[PDB]
Image (spheres, coloured by chain):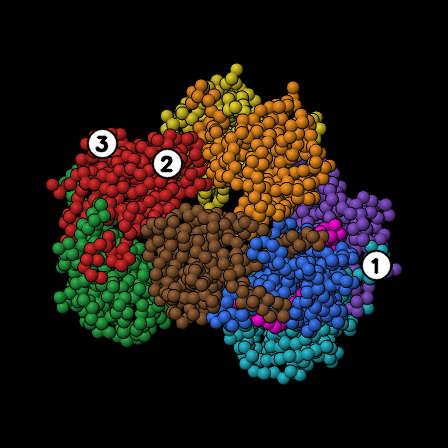
Chain colours: A red, B green, C orange, D brown, E blue, F yellow, G purple, H cyan
Amino acid sequence: MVKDEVIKQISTPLTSPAFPRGPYKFHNREYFNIVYRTDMDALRKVVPEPLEIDEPLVRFEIMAMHDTSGLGCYTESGQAIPVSFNGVKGDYLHMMYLDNEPAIAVGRELSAYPKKLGYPKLFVDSDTLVGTLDYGKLRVATATMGYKHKALDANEAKDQICRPNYMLKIIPNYDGSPRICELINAKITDVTVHEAWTGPTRLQLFDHAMAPLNDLPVKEIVSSSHILADIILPRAEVIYDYLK
Amino acid sequence: MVKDEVIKQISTPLTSPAFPRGPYKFHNREYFNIVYRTDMDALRKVVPEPLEIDEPLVRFEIMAMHDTSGLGCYTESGQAIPVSFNGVKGDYLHMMYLDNEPAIAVGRELSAYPKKLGYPKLFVDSDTLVGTLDYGKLRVATATMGYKHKALDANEAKDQICRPNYMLKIIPNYDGSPRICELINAKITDVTVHEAWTGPTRLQLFDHAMAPLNDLPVKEIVSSSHILADIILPRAEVIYDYLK
Amino acid sequence: MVKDEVIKQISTPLTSPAFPRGPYKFHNREYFNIVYRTDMDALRKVVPEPLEIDEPLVRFEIMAMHDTSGLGCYTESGQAIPVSFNGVKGDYLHMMYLDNEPAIAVGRELSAYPKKLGYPKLFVDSDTLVGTLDYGKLRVATATMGYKHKALDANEAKDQICRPNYMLKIIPNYDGSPRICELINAKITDVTVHEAWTGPTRLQLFDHAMAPLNDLPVKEIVSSSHILADIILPRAEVIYDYLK
Amino acid sequence: MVKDEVIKQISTPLTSPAFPRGPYKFHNREYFNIVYRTDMDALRKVVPEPLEIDEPLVRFEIMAMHDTSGLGCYTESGQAIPVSFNGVKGDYLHMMYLDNEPAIAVGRELSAYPKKLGYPKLFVDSDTLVGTLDYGKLRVATATMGYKHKALDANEAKDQICRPNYMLKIIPNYDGSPRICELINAKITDVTVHEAWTGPTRLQLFDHAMAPLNDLPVKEIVSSSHILADIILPRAEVIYDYLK
Amino acid sequence: MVKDEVIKQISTPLTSPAFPRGPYKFHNREYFNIVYRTDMDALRKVVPEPLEIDEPLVRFEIMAMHDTSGLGCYTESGQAIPVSFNGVKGDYLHMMYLDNEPAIAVGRELSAYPKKLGYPKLFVDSDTLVGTLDYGKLRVATATMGYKHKALDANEAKDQICRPNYMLKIIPNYDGSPRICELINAKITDVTVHEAWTGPTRLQLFDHAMAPLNDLPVKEIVSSSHILADIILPRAEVIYDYLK
Amino acid sequence: MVKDEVIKQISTPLTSPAFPRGPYKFHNREYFNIVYRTDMDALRKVVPEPLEIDEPLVRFEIMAMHDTSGLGCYTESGQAIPVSFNGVKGDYLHMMYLDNEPAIAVGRELSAYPKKLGYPKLFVDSDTLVGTLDYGKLRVATATMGYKHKALDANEAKDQICRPNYMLKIIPNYDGSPRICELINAKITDVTVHEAWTGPTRLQLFDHAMAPLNDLPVKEIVSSSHILADIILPRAEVIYDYLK
Amino acid sequence: MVKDEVIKQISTPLTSPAFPRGPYKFHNREYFNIVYRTDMDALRKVVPEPLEIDEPLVRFEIMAMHDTSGLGCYTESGQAIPVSFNGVKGDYLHMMYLDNEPAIAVGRELSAYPKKLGYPKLFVDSDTLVGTLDYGKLRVATATMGYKHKALDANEAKDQICRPNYMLKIIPNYDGSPRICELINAKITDVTVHEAWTGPTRLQLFDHAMAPLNDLPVKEIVSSSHILADIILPRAEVIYDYLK
Amino acid sequence: MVKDEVIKQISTPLTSPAFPRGPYKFHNREYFNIVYRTDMDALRKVVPEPLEIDEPLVRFEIMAMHDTSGLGCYTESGQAIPVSFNGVKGDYLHMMYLDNEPAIAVGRELSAYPKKLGYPKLFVDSDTLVGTLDYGKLRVATATMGYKHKALDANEAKDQICRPNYMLKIIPNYDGSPRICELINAKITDVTVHEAWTGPTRLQLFDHAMAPLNDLPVKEIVSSSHILADIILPRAEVIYDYLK
């Protein structure tokens, strides 16, 4: 193709790009969130400055993407860490694992989502909502909730989804030196919450060197939610440039 | 972690990066290459200017990576196109598909390899070297060669491996506009050829929208090679900036 | 657990009760009803005084509970018997078999549903709405309908759902003595019917000592319905105390 | 059965007809259409007079019938051909394959759909919409689309669904002589388009004597759509009698 | 396809008809017949005027079509009902279930066999000639015979095969109106019986809404035969027009 | 059923009760008990007043019911907690899981056992006694003992079997208000201990919201026993009414 | 083998007889008996003169032979018919189906048990004592009992086991002539009953030409027992010679 | 059943005899015979007086009964021994194993075949005819022949089929004393040999206490034949009474 056409391409493979252009509509995104108290100095080592930590909390998540335009039908699981930047609170995205490569690619290269390949699953096991997570062939997370035991306020749930997401864009130069090293912010604005629930909740984690979720071990379950919502993936913007 | 320690990290997840720092040492990389003639009109649409086409040729590839340091043990398959940049002959990398995420992300984010997720396999079917490629659950390529029928010159094999690799680096901004749009060269220089063969060779392609290898259909098999080698991944150089 | 807090729990295990507190919102409850003619003599034995039998009818049911708040996703199958109490027409709840233990406990202990463990399956076999029931490993009932062959009046379907349900609560004393031997009424009020259908319908039953549905043999199929509906199951009310 | 009752049955078997009376309501019918260029000569052989061809176009279809009143849950795949009848553009129904016999029977005997037995499947393979068709044990069609990559106008999708369908009704006399030989028209009137999408699209075909889709080989992909809709099966009308 | 050539085709799809032109040579057709006593009341409803019932008999059949010219290799199972038309004794064809779609189409559209899709199996289980019928996934009939226990008169077997078959052709107009409502006669003439056997025989039936063979229950087994024979199926003849 | 007969049935379904009358004779009941230390805080939350804790002890149990008259053959697993009631030491029954519904029903409704549905297995893995517990599809407990490494006194084992069991009987009214809320006592009277053993012993637990055994985590293994015995299910007696 | 030694062998093959010499010690023989009411007319045909029928009863049996000296481990199922000979009440042995060929041979050739090959299974399906019988691949009988629901009088069980068994020895001459047509009596004397139980009991039968148990249909379940016992099967005695 | 009817039944079970009356027509009986040398001492032990041995020969057989009237479809394997009776050469029937009980029963009780239960298979393994025999789950015989390598005279094959078969009929009295002890002769009279073949031939045997073919071990292979034929089961005749 001619130079003026290659410039209009979002990514490569040139004629079959890793991901298409947005917007990316997550119809019926099913969240299963668990906030838990972990080890403070293990958490401290993991959260990048200048982000601030109040309580030693982690939000484990498993998300069923039932119908995502452009990307497909996949599941995602990982840890977000409740923090604040210049007083403004939100979740720092620590690590995420999912079974859809275009979704991995679009998250890492258009935004700054800390994505790796993993095999998560969300389903109902009779009376229990079970979410699992594998890395390769090994189990790393088994989350459980009593199925829709108590109703949650759809507005507070809407506020939960809408919290700012802070992430790190780290891209090297061709020789390995830093090219982009940046703290970023994305906040969801297009949301509809169909239902929001909670109930008795546990989180079992196992050690894995490439999916090291249990580096922040669960010391106590604090809160949890099971949410059905429609969202549109938000645009990220730089809030802190480490390259002075 | 502290500000000065974050800038030292090569990628994200911050405490478990998508890939480690290299060098990435490919011990016993097994090549199965197939040079074939295709439609000129189809080829021309796919190759980006200012790269030039001589004969309408395509090099189909499948690579077994038995032992890659940093990355693991995986398989790779795709198409490279013989081209020219200011007279200098090399391969333009059109598309490639592999079953290892660290290798996908290192190639896409450290260099500019046109990589997607796919499921290739290389094996010997009694008397025939067989290379297959799947995308998802669907077969897209089946390559066959009579097993080690004719020895090839090891130095000619070395010369095939060491030619320039032309690539497009295409990264969007947060808003979807062009951030990077460059042609690069990665010439490979650190190589040991252990053995090299050829034989009767044939390539069967099938249509797939997300792995469109058959957009360059096989009209004629020109040549082929089966090469076992140790190489080191080379760094890229920018050679043409499309963003002027 | 403090004495006051013990008293506030609905059930046992104390810190993980057999079932949670309501309301239980049955979302997309799918009914497959088959009313049929049986032996009056067999019916007589089965129906307890003071409930009155008119015609010798049995309503066979298989329910798919696709999304039940607090209980989960499960299927239930059984027999209701059209009766009257003090001239008021309702269904007597004869026997029910279920897939979900919380759903059995809550039904047996918060209300008075005659529930046992069983393995029902409602599905469409291409052509046909199929409902099956197993007790243990053994098949006891196979229900068939020509898929959505004729539309039913939705208001008439609501009326069929909103009729009284007569059930026997029978709880022994620790010594085997009668302690609670009550007849109860539960009548659904909060209902939305989404669709209602008939079609050519058949019912095949098999003899089983622990799920003896065939103690009431099918002599003639009288009517049938396939209803999808949202309900909230009602508060029970004692209407006759056998022990007074 | 009384003569008068015999006469008011729609079909046979008399007491269990091959299909029930309509209307047949298609809830959430899911379309995957692929318009492509074929060889003009091959297409001419196939299209019956008086229908006229402009461009050598074929519409490959795979349709998932998630919930069809009277017929059930099934899948259909085949080819329609854009034609005109005396200046009125429509789709000629060439050949269709389904895994539901009531649907084949009603399609062939109430209307005039060119229906045979076959085994289609529509499913999301992570990032790709996949339609397949088998005849008996053999694969004949594999269709792929990048999952919902681009939004199509709902009205434009509706206009496509509502294009006249031209069908041949060909019934022999008992001696094998022509009894009925008509071109009919059916046109969808009741429609709700829920969503419509496009994206990169490929169609792979294989030769089969009894499902010879590949007699109209894929030369170029022209357009594609992925649509969910509610429709009622249209009433057919004779537009051309071959025996008058 | 030219207008004249369209008229010459027996069926549709036009270029790949549901069935080919005859004759259809049934080579090594294997019959397993069981005549039995049922309820006369049930029989009455099922048999259409002006056909006359004498004794309340049903001929259950399972046929293995080992080698049928133009149609293939397949199995069929159903019910014939011994009747008379104008004093002439024949079998009324009540319901038939088959394994082969061309065989269903040709029977329904070139003649008037009451055919639906089903899954029959005729086999010898060591001891016993076993014939089974499934509709969809569900078992509806299991037939057993002591293997070739007693030889039958071959000429008497030919006579049983060569009797008239009375069938109802019922084809609606596009609007649901009666168009063809004919009673027909087909009588086999070209027959070679290779063997004929009886033995102790039983028939087990199960209730199914879409294959309701058990609407005619087995009350007593009257006679039985196991015949291997070559036949050519006959031209049908209208004998009574309900619409005249 | 006559009113008088209704009153003499122990449970419901009326003509097929959830459980039969006793006595329930446990032939060759096989015990695997593991007493261990847990966190005192976690244990206090769990134990109801007026029961008192000395040391932070938990008895994990898995019991194979090889032959239980009235109930059948099944397995049970759970936790009992050593406590005292007004100076009388006994085991508080915390939570139990079984794969037999008659046993759950009788346990919950005749007595006051904290029974839920679960899938335990007791088996010898060559040189190790293994007890496992699953809730639904998820593993929650894995217990191991060196097979019969050391002999336990039969009388001392009998004394342990005969320790008072303290249970909560908690039944709601129809509106969900407290109806029955009692601490009861059951104490085994008929016993024959056939053999009793100990050996090295470990207990591995996993978190599950609906089977939360790991809320009482294993800090140290204190003692263990492997016992086979014959017992009769004890009659329960109220010792503390919470509503008086 | 010397002429004198030939004469000393009980059966054939000469050097490996179909069965060994007795006594045959049935250790832990487990009986599952179901006596039921059937058609007297059907019974009449089945019972041979001079044996007398009182009430129309059939004793269905399934026996598990856990440890039988000389024969092995196997299961048998069949029908006994309560009769009298010269006023002496016993069971007539109607048909028996077995899992062990030595056990069939010895029963048919050393005594006169009406034995055929069949596949019985007695097991406890959690809740329920299940006994099944297959002939070849086909299910013919499914028996169920509520597991050990009520204890029986062991002496009364011994009496039921110790009653006379009337059997027909029928051996043709080589030419098909009657050679032995004797009625025989065998009455167990050496018996130890270990346990005896009843419970709610059902029997489901299916039609099969070679195992026609359902020629005697279940009209009403009269009584039932589950007995474990040691026996030594008795010497037979001719009581009536049809040929004299 | 009337006494007179009782007397005209061939066997028992009375109303479902172990076998029907003949003649038993063996259509396409397929033979695989292997004559071999064994140890003379072992063979002498095995052969009953008055039958005489010349050379130490054994005929191993495996016979596929593709279509046997009255009995069904089954396979038989065993050993016959060339002997003479008072100067008339024939085959002594040593031991036979089959997977059809009617065939064992008729064989043992109408005639005097030394039949036990076993599992033979005759099949072509590409280039080799294979006969196997299992007793229960254990392999006892594996026979191979180069497939139809050489043509045998049809008449010579017929002469071999028609060799007298000598059999022991050994039935005990009820007390285990000799009742019948006869040497009989059966000789095939109705035969059509369709084809006969030989070729390289091997026989591998394994020791089994209940199928002890290897008590006559293979020392040398002498001859072999592969024959298909139609025969009628011969009528037997006593030639030597051991008790006269």
Identify the secondary structure beneath mark 1.
helix
Q: CA distance from mark 1 to mark 2?
A: 82 Å
The residue shown at (58%, 63%) is E105
Q: Identity of the amino acid at label 2?
A: Val
Q: Which mark is residue A88?
A: 3
**Of circles 1 and 3, which is in front?**
3
Q: In the image, F38: left or right of F160?
A: left
Q: CA distance from mark 3 to mark 2?
A: 24 Å
Identify the secondary structure beneath mark 3.
strand
Asked if the residue under mark 2 is in contact with the one under mark 3, i.e. CB atoms within 8 Å, the reply is no
- Tell me which corner region of the image, top left, top right, bottom left or bottom right, holds residue H177: bottom right
Does H190 sit above or below residue A144?
Answer: below
Q: Identity of the amino acid at label 1?
A: Glu
Where does residue C216 sit, x and y in percent of width and height? 68, 40
The residue shown at (20%, 68%) is B53
Q: Magenta region: which residues?
A: E16-45
Does B89 sit above or below residue A39?
Answer: below
Q: Which mark is residue A193?
A: 2
Mark 3 vs 2, N-terminal side: 3
Q: Label 3 neighbourhood size at 10 Å, few (<14), some (14-19), many (20+)?
A: few
Where does residue B23 sit, x and y in percent of width and height? 18, 55
Q: Which mark is residue H5?
A: 1
- Tell me which corner region of the image, top left, top right, bottom left or bottom right, holds residue D80: bottom left
